[PDB]
Amino acid sequence: SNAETVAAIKTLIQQLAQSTDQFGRAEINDALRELQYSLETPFDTVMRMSLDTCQVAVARIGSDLGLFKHLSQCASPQSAEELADHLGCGRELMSRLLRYMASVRMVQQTDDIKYISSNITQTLAVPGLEAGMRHAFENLWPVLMALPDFLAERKYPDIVDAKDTAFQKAFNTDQDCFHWLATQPTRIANFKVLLTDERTPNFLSTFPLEKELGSWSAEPEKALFVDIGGGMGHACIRLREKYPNQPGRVILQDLPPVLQAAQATLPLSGIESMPHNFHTPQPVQGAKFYFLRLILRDFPDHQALEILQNIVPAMDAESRIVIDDGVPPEKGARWAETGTDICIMSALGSKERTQRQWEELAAKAGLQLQALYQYTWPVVNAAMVFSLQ
Amino acid sequence: SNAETVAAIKTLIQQLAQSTDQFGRAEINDALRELQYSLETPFDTVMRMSLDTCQVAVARIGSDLGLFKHLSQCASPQSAEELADHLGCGRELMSRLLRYMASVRMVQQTDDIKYISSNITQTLAVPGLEAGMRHAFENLWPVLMALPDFLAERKYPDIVDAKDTAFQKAFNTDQDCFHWLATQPTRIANFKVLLTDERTPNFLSTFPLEKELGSWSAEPEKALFVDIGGGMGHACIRLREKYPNQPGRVILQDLPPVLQAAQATLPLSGIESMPHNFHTPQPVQGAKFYFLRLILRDFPDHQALEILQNIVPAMDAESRIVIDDGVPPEKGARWAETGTDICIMSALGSKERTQRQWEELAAKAGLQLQALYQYTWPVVNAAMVFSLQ
Amino acid sequence: SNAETVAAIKTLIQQLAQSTDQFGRAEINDALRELQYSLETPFDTVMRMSLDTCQVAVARIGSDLGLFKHLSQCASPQSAEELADHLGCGRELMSRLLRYMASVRMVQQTDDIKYISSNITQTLAVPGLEAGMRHAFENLWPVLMALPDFLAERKYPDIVDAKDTAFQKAFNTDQDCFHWLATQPTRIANFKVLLTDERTPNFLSTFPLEKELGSWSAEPEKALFVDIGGGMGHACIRLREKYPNQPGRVILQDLPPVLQAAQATLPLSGIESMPHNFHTPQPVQGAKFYFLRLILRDFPDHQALEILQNIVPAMDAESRIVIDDGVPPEKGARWAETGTDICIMSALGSKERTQRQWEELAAKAGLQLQALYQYTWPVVNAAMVFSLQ
Amino acid sequence: SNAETVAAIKTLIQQLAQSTDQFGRAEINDALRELQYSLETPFDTVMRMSLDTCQVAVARIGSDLGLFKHLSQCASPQSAEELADHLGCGRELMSRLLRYMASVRMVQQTDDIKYISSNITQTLAVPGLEAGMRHAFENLWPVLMALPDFLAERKYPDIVDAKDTAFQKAFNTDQDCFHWLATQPTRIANFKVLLTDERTPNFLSTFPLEKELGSWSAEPEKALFVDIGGGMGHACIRLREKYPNQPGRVILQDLPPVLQAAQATLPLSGIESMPHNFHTPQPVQGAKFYFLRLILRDFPDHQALEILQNIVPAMDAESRIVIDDGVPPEKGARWAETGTDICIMSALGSKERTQRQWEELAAKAGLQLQALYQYTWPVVNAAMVFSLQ
Ligand SMILES: C[S@@+](CC[C@H](N)C(=O)[O-])C[C@H]1O[C@@H](n2cnc3c(N)ncnc32)[C@H](O)[C@@H]1O
Ligand SMILES: C[S@@+](CC[C@H](N)C(=O)[O-])C[C@H]1O[C@@H](n2cnc3c(N)ncnc32)[C@H](O)[C@@H]1O
Ligand SMILES: C[S@@+](CC[C@H](N)C(=O)[O-])C[C@H]1O[C@@H](n2cnc3c(N)ncnc32)[C@H](O)[C@@H]1O
Ligand SMILES: C[S@@+](CC[C@H](N)C(=O)[O-])C[C@H]1O[C@@H](n2cnc3c(N)ncnc32)[C@H](O)[C@@H]1O
Ligand SMILES: C/C=C/C=C/CCC[C@H](C)C(=O)c1c(O)c(-c2ccccc2)c[nH]c1=O
Ligand SMILES: C/C=C/C=C/CCC[C@H](C)C(=O)c1c(O)c(-c2ccccc2)c[nH]c1=O
Ligand SMILES: C/C=C/C=C/CCC[C@H](C)C(=O)c1c(O)c(-c2ccccc2)c[nH]c1=O
Ligand SMILES: C/C=C/C=C/CCC[C@H](C)C(=O)c1c(O)c(-c2ccccc2)c[nH]c1=O
Ligand SMILES: [Cl-]
Ligand SMILES: [Cl-]
Ligand SMILES: [Cl-]
Ligand SMILES: [Cl-]
Ligand SMILES: [Cl-]
Ligand SMILES: [Cl-]
Ligand SMILES: [Cl-]
Ligand SMILES: [Cl-]
Ligand SMILES: [Cl-]
Ligand SMILES: [Cl-]
Ligand SMILES: [Cl-]
Ligand SMILES: [Cl-]
Ligand SMILES: [Cl-]
Ligand SMILES: [Cl-]
Ligand SMILES: [Cl-]
Ligand SMILES: [Cl-]
Ligand code: NA
Ligand code: NA
Ligand code: NA
Ligand code: NA
């Protein structure tokens, strides 16, 4: 029986998944995708590409309605009628949306055709993750929609400039993306929520702090850690939590509105909040670690180089710049890192960088790679430690 | 070891897939998708929704470049540089596109970092399947991009009318989709190619023609099969191929430009090409089978009913209307049929119909269901045989 | 490809086995056996039954030669010639024995046609486990060889009596097995070694000792645990190890030659060694637990009842008799417990007992079951706690 | 859940087994055995070796009772009581035997504790396969039981002589096995039934007869095929069935009592029955094929050589001796061929032979190997074609 075979595959892959760690589960998931793509018929390939688009549109509708938050806190299954009436949605529309969501596990449909939350329901109810989905819909979709004709009309240029990529066509503007976004209050508000998401694991799981410090002295009033564009300060928080007795100032640098949003959740002491624009010279002199997490991927080389050149003059011989970012391999890169590469090309003019590309960029700033500490697999994020050449 | 476990999973799934038929492979593939969604982390869920969008955009670029057709006819692996120079693409852009494509199996990357075709490459090189992907990009994505704000602005109405859905917002028109498309030659050209795709399997794999025929006589000069909106006439061609000895007229009905396109590949004899607008009364009297394949799903009830009411007066007691279309279940419907439902709601105002919904529609035309012959699984397509009530 | 499928099956089963515990691995192993028997051809079934016999005979030869102990301490693969010369075996005989052993994993053969130890090699090198294999060869096989003609000659009687079973035919004696064995020094010597094997896990893994103890007082000088026929005293040793702070006498009871063998490995204090024949009245009065592990399975009902009736008069109201033995289910019993049943029927006239059969036996002694604490699965061993009725 | 995992393993291995051929299923079965042996605990290893012995003893009892034949023709499940009364067995004995048989799939136990035939029940009801099991019990078991002490008392000699192996100790005789068996009427009767079993597949599935014949002419009255020790003549029958129009005499040679038993099932014409002792000179001169299937494995080299030397003088340059027998590999031999090797060593003084060992034996008769045609895997049986040197 087909049904018996399918259920047996599910049982065995679930047991295997439970028996490994998060990195092993990520490897299994990538293999399931690869299997799916190799076993689909030609028609199925086009149907998948045609319809998987629906998920973000329907998640955006569920978010607008508050459906995922509401379902995540219901204690019993809800009918489509009950959901429609509670959330202010046409009843037939709600029923069709729910049937679609259940078919892609965005909710669960029960045997009596009522609806309960799934793992994905709970995910889309989390503010920061919801904001990620909303960002995909309102910022990524339009640049991807513009990219093919942008490239066709321009005879397939290498994209190298944040002011000359698909974003300008998609939003009918000559501004670059970051400048334009700063003029759009609802879009800024969504980024504020997005910053509350904290990725796990983080670089402290493999960063050999005591080894990298050696005999470094914090006196007088030297900074241990300067978190440049640190957002809510998650890296500073985790550093203080893991090494509470390590001397040295721990400093969160960001723009004033982000620092203001960070205050409610920062510790009352031990982490300084310092307004600082990272396109301007670094004020903190001689720090041990100048930390850039998921900053430089958003900039083409010219701008990324300028960000580094604003830090290098503040370094002493013991200082290090730590770039915590994606490091895709030379070959066999996975969809999460190549897809990111295409999206940030189209919106930002930037790119994912291999280790050798990071080293070439840093050498232009007078920096040499001393160590690289991977902390996620198989898609690699790593803390790259650079010193003055 | 975890690599070894992943390779063993692939080996076993590949072997189970080869030991079943196409319907069993479709069930396995849906299971792999369900497993993937249940094993992903919350972050991975949002990453997948954010990035799976990239595939249609990049497939559209490769189609514009002629990459898939070129790679499918190459006899040896090609470097990114070779492909970029041949196709007229910036070398860095080409390399980045190819790395993304290899990561989603749109091409395959070799250990030498060169590129060969995959199953998906070959699929996207086929004109009719390529046209389906291009249709998703240029027609479906704009209406899905418009749907959430359309619904929000209108306070979530049940969509019931082809003239009042997301299409009018997406394309800034008051026309319905079909009327607007007829004014857009480049889109018309893509639909012309899309009509050359023939779906497999088809209803003749399970339709018990001799049983449904009974003792119907083709004498003196009666019509066996009238293919209403038959496109290229594939159903007529397959009918004559499978039943070469059954007498009676076999008639392809469509609009003149489509009949003209059909002529080159119709048999030289045995199939008549009759121009006929199915919004007007059916001219062929007393045919055994009036066949509507994938026609009525494109219309809301009011218009679908009109199409049926145009046929009913031509029927005699032995005539049957055969609706060949999707028949999703009452519960547990799959993503291909619910995703289709959301898309045709958004572009056409129409809907997928369960068996009970098909029967209710047909009853309004004075028709009763006699038999239903499924021919695909697990997503249901079936030939529904209706007679006069 | 079929090689690849077989390797993938091994990889997946090995991984599932490592992800569970010993009871789950035992369930997997029984499943593999059931699969083997259902997939074999009729010829293969007869070949398996004909040849699996070879394993005990060849293990007995390797034990005689000292092969398993020698190979288990070798640091490099050994050739057949090296092993034959070292152990004093004909070179061709040795090579043929080793090829047979490697084919059933009793040793492993390398790609260079040399030999190293396997898990089974190490097992057969352990004195107590080796002695179990030697017991099967010299005591069990003769009684199984005699059983079919014993039954045929006697017209298939229910075997009820230790003095009238297959043992008397096998060994040409009118003595019962236990009485005969006491006259056979080489067999006695093997049993002495077999007693040093300690089974794992044991009842203390699940026995809720503090709950069963309640408020029992060891004062003034009462007995906590009387191990009746305790052999080397493993239960006493493990009890004192797990419950080092529970007061009360812990007493090992057995016959003098066995107590003398136990002395070298008993703790220096805390466990008394008391000679006692369990066919005579229990001398220790009012103990909390009188413990019988794998004793009563060796006796038919009449004699097993006598052993219990010898203990009952020593019991006070808080005393309990704890039978630790096999408890096969009413249906679906596994080969280890039914194979044991046939063997002890044939040698000893006794039987495995279900829970209901244990309760019926104990009721004849005036005892009632209070609790049953399973500690192995799927083959059931359990500590059954009985009190005065 | 363990039960869910185990059921899923069973489902997947059954589906994989169905999807391959008989040789692939044999490979899966050997892998399941290997998995079982590597995953068992040390105690489980000794319990398996101790108890798997029970299967042949209990099958012999079921055979004596007629249980397997009776159950194989019952149309409903039978209780132990019904079986006991019908077959003349003590009721408790029958119930215990059935529980044991069900635990090793020799019968099936139902949920209401009644009994139905399994695949193995049906196998043990087939006369020739039943006779194989009975042969294992009455002829193989005693020589295996005698082998360890035979080898110990003789200081581990290479066994090379049919008159000096374990058989003489086991049966207290100076005769060799074949001579002694010919004096034992019940044992002869069992061999008569055993000869009715026909192994599948056979050498004609891969033997390129037309290629090996070339331009061979059958005139005058030449023999195509002389089946030396051909038993019931299955090889002659299959040859005539597959090549009905091939000229040349087809001759079955065996001893008179076997030829007599063969007459009832031989074709009425086209196969000659010729009494002939293969320890005497071959009477048929110049035959194309002198065929020896499973003959020479039963003889030490000296006797096997004599059998060949009785044929070689009858050969002309076109004649071939075809040895159809086991050809174990140089390394990695499987249990069915090494177990056979140990059994025939112990009973017959003979041995399994690798290809190189067959060639060394045949060269002593003045023969050279021209071709070898395998027809079973992974345990190899092959038709080896030899010509005069
Ligand atoms: C991708 S978020 C990275 C946050 C943080 N590094 C982390 O991983 O937890 C980019 C951050 O850069 C900050 N940012 C953007 N432009 C900046 C600028 N010109 N100067 C300082 N911070 C800036 C944003 O406010 C935001 O917090
Ligand atoms: C989904 S397509 C092709 C379906 C076709 N029955 C098949 O399955 O092979 C719909 C068809 O309806 C035709 N069509 C659209 N409007 C029509 C009309 N008013 N009258 C007749 N045919 C029409 C199109 O030209 C097209 O060939
Ligand atoms: C299966 S063995 C060891 C069982 C032991 N209870 C254990 O599980 O560790 C049976 C024990 O009963 C002992 N035994 C046999 N007959 C006895 C008797 N009449 N009185 C006391 N002990 C006896 C043997 O000496 C042996 O130690
Ligand atoms: C293992 S059976 C093989 C039967 C046959 N070759 C087959 O594979 O179908 C051995 C055969 O050799 C025959 N045999 C034994 N001794 C013989 C002898 N001295 N001369 C001729 N046949 C003999 C037996 O009667 C029996 O038929
Ligand atoms: C909260 C969880 C979110 C899961 C997200 C997967 C994100 C994939 C996504 C392409 C991504 O990576 C990045 C961006 O979109 C952007 C950006 C920023 C502003 C405008 C457009 C794009 C910058 N830099 C990135 O890296
Ligand atoms: C060759 C394979 C092609 C796959 C194409 C996409 C299949 C999914 C896709 C939603 C689908 O089904 C349908 C349509 O898009 C449309 C339509 C027609 C015109 C405009 C917009 C939509 C009508 N009716 C449908 O049913
Ligand atoms: C009907 C199905 C039977 C399945 C059988 C597996 C048979 C294994 C079995 C050791 C085997 O092979 C052979 C013999 O016992 C003998 C023999 C013949 C006479 C006396 C003792 C042994 C000869 N020659 C063999 O080869
Ligand atoms: C170290 C592992 C050893 C495994 C040994 C074989 C386990 C199976 C085995 C049938 C078993 O269980 C029992 C006996 O043989 C006997 C016995 C004792 C004396 C003579 C004959 C049998 C008693 N009572 C049993 O229960
Ligand atoms: Cl929101
Ligand atoms: Cl809301
Ligand atoms: Cl660390
Ligand atoms: Cl095109
Ligand atoms: Cl829009
Ligand atoms: Cl299809
Ligand atoms: Cl026909
Ligand atoms: Cl549904
Ligand atoms: Cl020993
Ligand atoms: Cl006997
Ligand atoms: Cl155990
Ligand atoms: Cl304690
Ligand atoms: Cl049972
Ligand atoms: Cl018989
Ligand atoms: Cl009988
Ligand atoms: Cl052939
Ligand atoms: Na409802
Ligand atoms: Na409608
Ligand atoms: Na009894
Ligand atoms: Na019964």
Image (spheres, coloured by chain):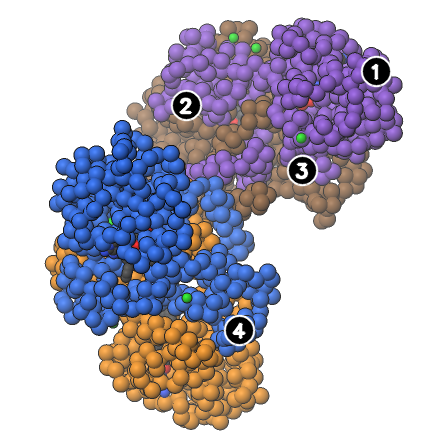
Chain colours: A orange, B blue, C brown, D purple
Report the disc number at residue D285: 1
Q: Is residue D32 above or below residue B30?
A: above
The kind of residue on which mark 4 rests is Ala
| SS at mark 4 in the image | helix
Determine if marks 1 and 4 fall on one subunit: no
Label 2 crowd (10 A; few <14 / some 14-19 / many >=20): many
User: What residue did someone put label 2 on?
Assistant: D109
Report the disc number at residue B84: 4
Indicate the position of residue A28 as horizontal and vertical percent values. 46, 56
Residue occupying the far front of the picture = B220
Determine if marks 2 and 4 fall on one subunit: no
The kind of residue on which mark 2 rests is Gln
Closest to the observer: C320 or C14? Answer: C14
| SS at mark 2 in the image | strand
Disc 2 residue: CB within 8 Å of ligand 21: yes
| SS at mark 3 in the image | helix
The kind of residue on which mark 3 rests is Ala
